[PDB]
Length: 140
Image (tube, rainbow, N blue to C red; front, top):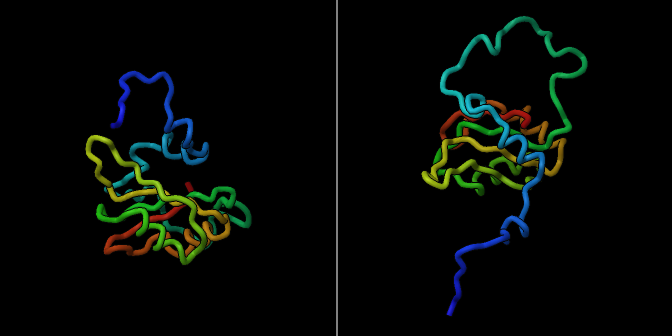
């Protein structure tokens, strides 16, 4: 009843669906080590005085995508969306999954429709316990 084809000159899925330049550049060009860390180093972050960032700068508001790591393997896109939904409206959740293993490593990125809620999510749950594990959130 159904006919199948072997060789295909053009792709139907790629033509019909496409990914944004912002999500593609951040996810594809991310550092293999920075994407996931097992041991914490004091050299990267050090405690000092009350100042540091200053009056201007420090945090960016131009990006609406945030990094979220430290989740459980049994967590789905629905879980990440519904957990970060109280802060604002969310567009899409991406989880780097391999075709061979089809397994999750406990980290993903979140896309926020509003830039104000995005900055709110980072200031409220930057280092909080979710699903029984510690998570980290920052600008992507």
